[PDB]
Amino acid sequence: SKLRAVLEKLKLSRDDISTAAGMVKGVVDHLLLRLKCDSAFRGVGLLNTGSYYEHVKISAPNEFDVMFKLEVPRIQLEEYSNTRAYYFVKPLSQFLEGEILSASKMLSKFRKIIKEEITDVIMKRKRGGSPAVTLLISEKISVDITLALESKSSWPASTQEGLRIQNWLSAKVRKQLRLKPFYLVPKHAKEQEETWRLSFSHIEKEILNNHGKSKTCCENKEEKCCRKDCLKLMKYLLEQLKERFKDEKHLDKFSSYHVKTAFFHVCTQNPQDSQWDRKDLGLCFDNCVTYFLQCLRTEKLENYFIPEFNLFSSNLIDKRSKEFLTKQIEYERNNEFPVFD
Ligand SMILES: Nc1ncnc2c1ncn2[C@@H]1O[C@H](COP(=O)(O)OP(=O)(O)NP(=O)(O)O)[C@@H](O)[C@H]1O
Ligand SMILES: COCC(=O)N1CCc2[nH]c3c(Cl)c(Cl)ccc3c2[C@@H]1C
Ligand SMILES: [Mg+2]
Ligand SMILES: [Mg+2]
Ligand SMILES: [Zn+2]
């Protein structure tokens, strides 16, 4: 089919994987070692996150996401201004502003050490908003390194009704996942440079790499579902539209995380592996496209872990920009996705 041919073109070359994985490893492992020399970052450890480690990276292995996490014992959080996702947190004294541990102070020292420690490896110009320090290896491979505080405490109350996976992955899996740590990354609330942001990237990876109702989903030829193929196609649809419309400000604020989040909700809506049969790829992809269009139309895209954090709030994305993306995605759906050609 046309969609199968798209998926074929989006496959990663084994040779590119071998080269890129080796280059990323050498840089990451080196910075890990060097940060451990600093009194503040002694305890950093690696967590691999994002689409490469979820096996949904498309086209080229040219962008990798990692967390350098630090266990902070005795963490005490205070939710910032009913935002549900942003928190105050109360060798680390250098980062205290009062009794709060300043996210911006920690991020600035983290960035400064990496910049000094960095194979042709450069640091990309600071992007506002992002919690990451971003590197570029050999002019081609981007690496986002996100500092994170690790907490082994119970997840914050704003997550109590999130992760609605009980009919898909099971109640016992939901309980096991909520016994894992959670993370705080230095992305600040709109106003607040002291605040941190909840992150569950590690749980997103666990879900995508163990994604079936059947434990043997995608382990044999009889159970090769099309979940990851549908996420890849949604990602490519948004990627291509953002490229075509790169000079149109209306597409600036959309990201692959909006389609990842919508995808997780469609998995909740369609929990059975038989709703993701390979033979139904076009229908499954359409289910994902129509769900995303409904999210745009209703201005509703809840964070999968934090339901009262709406990614499609008018506070974050103007109605006009969602309507613009609706228009372009409807055109694609109505014309058999010419942007894929
Ligand atoms: N807005 C967000 N809210 C929460 N977590 C986010 C957000 N944006 C990115 N992340 C996390 O950071 C990871 C890497 O971000 P990004 O590199 O932008 O996306 P990806 O999932 O890696 N897809 P891509 O790199 O586009 O193939 C995502 O997988 C999420 O786990
Ligand atoms: C092309 O890649 C960009 C990317 O990877 N990011 C930029 C935007 C963003 N926003 C985040 C939030 Cl809100 C949380 Cl909780 C955790 C991680 C992120 C990230 C990452 C570092
Ligand atoms: Mg990525
Ligand atoms: Mg990234
Ligand atoms: Zn599967």
Image (cartoon, rainbow, N blue to C red):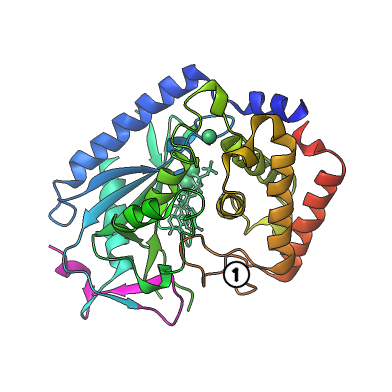
Residue 85 belongs to the span the image colors magenta = yes
Q: Residue at x 60, y 41 (%)?
A: 231
Q: Residue at x 70, y 26 (%)?
A: 4
Residue situated furthest right in the rendering: 335
Is 200 drawn above or below residue 55 in the view shown? below
Q: Quadrant of residue 98?
A: bottom left
Instruction: Categorize mark 1 by other alpha carbons within 10 Å: few (<14), some (14-19), many (20+).
Output: few
* Horizontal arrangement in the rendering, residue 3 relative to residue 262 (left or right): right
Residue 273 belongs to the span the image colors magenta = no
> Observer-nearest residue: 294 or 28?
294
Q: Residue at x 59, y 52 (%)?
A: 255
Q: Which residue is mark 1?
A: 316
- Tell me, yes or no, if residue 194 can be seen here: no
Q: Quadrant of the C terminus?
A: top right
- Tell me, yes or no, if residue 251 can be seen here: yes
Q: Position of residue 146 (x, y in %)?
A: 36, 52
Q: Residues in magenta? A: 79-98
Q: Position of residue 114 (x, y in %)?
A: 29, 47
Q: Residue at x 56, y 65 (%)?
A: 302
Element at badge 1? loop
Q: Amino acid at mark 1?
A: Leu
Q: Quadrant of the N terminus?
A: top right
